[PDB]
Image (spheres, coloured by chain):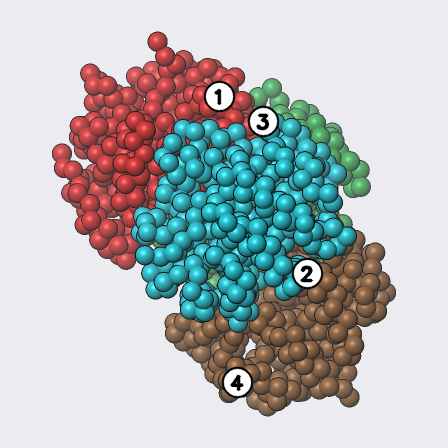
Chain colours: A brown, B green, C red, D cyan
Amino acid sequence: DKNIIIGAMTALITPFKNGKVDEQSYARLIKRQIENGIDAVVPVGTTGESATLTHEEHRTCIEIAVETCKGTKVKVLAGAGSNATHEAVGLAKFAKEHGADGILSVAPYYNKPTQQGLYEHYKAIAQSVDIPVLLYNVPGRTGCEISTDTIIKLFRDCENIYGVKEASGNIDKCVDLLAHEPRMMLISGEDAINYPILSNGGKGVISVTSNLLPDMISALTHFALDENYKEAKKINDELYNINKILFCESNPIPIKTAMYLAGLIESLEFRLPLCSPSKENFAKIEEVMKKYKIKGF
Amino acid sequence: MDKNIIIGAMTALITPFKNGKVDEQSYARLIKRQIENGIDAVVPVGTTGESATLTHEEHRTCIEIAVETCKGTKVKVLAGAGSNATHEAVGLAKFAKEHGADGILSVAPYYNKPTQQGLYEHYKAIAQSVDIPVLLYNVPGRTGCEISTDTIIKLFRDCENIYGVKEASGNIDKCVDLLAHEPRMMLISGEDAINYPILSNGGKGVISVTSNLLPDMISALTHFALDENYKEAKKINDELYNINKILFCESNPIPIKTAMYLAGLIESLEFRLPLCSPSKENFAKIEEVMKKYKIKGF
Amino acid sequence: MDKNIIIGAMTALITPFKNGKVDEQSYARLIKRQIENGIDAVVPVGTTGESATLTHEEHRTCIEIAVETCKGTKVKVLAGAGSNATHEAVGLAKFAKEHGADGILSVAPYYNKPTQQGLYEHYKAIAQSVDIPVLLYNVPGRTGCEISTDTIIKLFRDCENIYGVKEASGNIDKCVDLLAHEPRMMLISGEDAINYPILSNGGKGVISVTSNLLPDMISALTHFALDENYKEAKKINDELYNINKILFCESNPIPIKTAMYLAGLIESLEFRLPLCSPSKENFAKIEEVMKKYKIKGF
Amino acid sequence: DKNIIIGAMTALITPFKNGKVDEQSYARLIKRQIENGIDAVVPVGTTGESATLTHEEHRTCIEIAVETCKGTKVKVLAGAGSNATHEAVGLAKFAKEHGADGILSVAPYYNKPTQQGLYEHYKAIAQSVDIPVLLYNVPGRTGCEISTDTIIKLFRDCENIYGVKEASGNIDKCVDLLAHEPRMMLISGEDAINYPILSNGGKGVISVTSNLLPDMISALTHFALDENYKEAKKINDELYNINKILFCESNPIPIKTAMYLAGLIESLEFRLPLCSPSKENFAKIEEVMKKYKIKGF
């Protein structure tokens, strides 16, 4: 096989305090993920508000995850994608330099490359580092889809591309992927359907919910990897309400709202154009939260 | 909620024509082939059976043939009986019950887009008119409407004989929603490519297009799943993916009838308009996918 | 001379029910009101007239009443006569001609998803069965299929009496596509909110829901545009925008029937299942928007 | 009341040569636009591959547009937008300093802000400069929609927001917009439907096709603005084939290909993730081009 990063993973939120990244809170939150069975953390993905961080903050966030995971079996899969290939290569190289175990690389958003463009984009990225690269498909945000054929070609042509995070609400595609190329690591990027993706041979999750409920997401994932499907589904069913409410408005608006209500971050603060949820949605999130046992620090 | 149910591996039967006429001999023969290959129920005159272009008497006849042919076996008959007019859907359900069907499959009203309130009243009226099991059938790509999860669960709870839903909506999230909130219902896969994922989440059957051609493979998949042998179920589901997709290269049942003709299982590649033969190109694509599969004869 | 066509401002008639039956006296009176308010043609038994839930006998009664009421006036009857079964659509087409219809509106097959080749043969069968004008009707959100621009153009060119299409697809790109490649056809708006843009691009009429309530406004709009008085046609389209949207807050004809009842134009708010009354919330929403419009009486 | 930029406008392609911006070609292309009746030019929009340009190349393009338009009545509506409000604000001021007459600012892509966030996003942009701001809605690329209510509110609350470029294939929305706020400048961002948008009160276009056929786009627009709808439609009808083929692959892949095929640029290069179209699409574009009279220099 190739070198891989799988298991229960968390797309880390990035707490702000008075506009500034709260780096002490960020380290604390990672330790909390670590203590609750999480296998890897994903600094500066979509959930971490990658769009609104400076390059230096981006790098710092990776550094913090790296430093915090040292001395543990937990890995850092650093968010490093861009819709400009030169920037994506740069971010990938930095991530490798700061000691990341691998990178998560979102499909170019907004500029809608063709399948050929996506292929050359990821081929260029994979060639720039000797560390694992997980592709990330999320057409609702990007405006483009990495097709199954392109994913499979990338996996077969590039040594370090080992799988894809799918956030596309398409279980047919998930079947297509693993039926034609069962060696790849399919990763769930959609919490509500973690179980179905794992039960089809998916080997991990990159989760939003796990920011709030890491013990539950890790237990779910580990049961499925142990083929204890009954237990995995049970947790998946249990988590459905919170998994959905965490998307009542665009992620990470609801998850930051939950983390704040839980006393886990200090300030319900975003960077524009993101902002507080509506009062209605704030109330729904707080209400759904009452059904769950939330781990403290 | 106890209810009486029809679950397991089920086939949405194609309806063969010979010179425009329903070939009833061929129909009975096809059903026997399903039976001998381990199928649990058959669905006469659903979408796959060209329900839209059969007369009412042909519709009744097909249900009748299914019931009679399945006599002397464990195989159940889940009769297609839906309509976008509530009075007709009720009439159809009543017919199905009188002809001895074990249950009915009742598609959401197509074309006229009833609201969720209307869907609830529609199905409640159907459900109240007969005491046999009713399976809801959601297929928004064909009907132009969606029975919401909330509407489905309400119907399941409020009407004793409504026991589940056939979903053909490519929506595994909804499948989770359904069974997480109401784990007593029978979720049935109406989409062959994703049979295994639905069953592994607690689905209890399939109503299959592919099983017309490969009943033994669809039956084995389903039964492996029900026995919690997920490895084997997934293995068959992965193997079938290619045939599962190509059977929808044009609108169902155009490809499956083409495959049945190519396999020598039906005599004539005939439809009733507005359905018609596939393109020569799709004809050849179907033929070449079939070659990767071992197709049971009579 | 002139090619035989039915165009201008046209109304998709609601079918009023009294105690479960077609209110015929109401029906005739409603058509009379359309006639007196500048309408060029009426459409009995379309989507808006709940065609799906009417019996064949009721379909007849509505068409006859329409024919009798327009008789001696310039106003034409473009009768609904489509089906997802070609043998039925042919029968319905002949049925409509024989009852005195000037032409037919024939919806694309719903639910069974014919291919473009199927649609072609479907409509060719229909067109050859009668000698009166045939208007195609594309509404993919309801039928689950699309008559492609290519298929519409080939049907228009190959069949004499197919003279155009009613588009209800929210797709102005297609409307440009149609009239750029085949400018001889009659593109008819089946979407009230965008009546003007369709007409400003060369469309030759509308088949309107809103005209049930405000026939004088819709006909004036259509005739301004037909006269290349685009400023005035737009002005009316703009002020009708609110009522045009609210009449679709729930599936048509649920809102338009609510509005007609509210206006005192029909005497019973009755639908046939699966259609039913709107929510209290939408009822009040409809009642409010109406307050901004001058509604003609009888 | 409200300074505006309307009329026939071109979303400029950015020619690359040996990986670099071809500054001489850029200038020559703009002159050609000017000489063919165009009312404004949009440097570094989507069609100009904004995503993959550096800040310095961005500056260079605007400066070249401004310098080349000097002494003409032709205006420079600069691409200046981002999915991070702080950057978007910075780009807006940066465009003003470099002499842009106005800015085109696209809805935040990828991070999917809420309508409340969109409102705050644009209000911050509008209040940071004193030149006209045109909103740009293109949900297929951004993954979000600026609602009619949000557009009208921004138009009414912020002095310099004067209109919106719509690329949403939604004439219903165009009706809604101009029915409720007929004072705004609705600008077509979808070449195929230029005429229907203009005939409903639209006051201009920001065109892709005008790169290749500027004389035709300008006449269409000016005919329409003068209420000669017959002539405006006639041209829109004739352009339909080319308007569609120029989107056979994602803009600007086809238009830059067409310009090269036409002999109007000397190299055909994109920045990854963009690339040349398929061989068969090269052929398709070429066949469609043969039906039009393409102005030289």
Residue B100 shown left or right of residue A100 in the figure: left
Instruction: Identify the chain of the residue marked 2, using the numbered disc in the image.
Output: A
Task: Please name the residue shown 69% across and 54% down the image.
Answer: D21
Tag 1: amino acid: Phe
Query: Residue beneath label 2, please?
Result: A84
The residue carrying mark 3 is: C117
Q: Amino acid at mark 3?
A: Gln
Left or right of residue D114: residue D247: right
Q: Secondary structure at mark 2?
A: loop
First of labels 1, 3 by sequence position: 3
The answer to whether mark 2 and mark 4 are in CB contact below 8 A is no
Q: Are marks 3 and 4 in contact (CB under 8 Å)?
A: no
Q: Position of residue B3 (x, y in %)?
A: 49, 58
Q: Quadrant of the N terminus of chain A?
A: bottom right
Element type at mark 3: helix
The residue at the point 66 percent across, 44 percent down is D256
Query: Mark 2 to mark 1: distance in Å?
Result: 48 Å
Question: Is residue D246 found left or right of C243 in the rendered image?
Answer: right
Chain letter, disc 4 residue: A
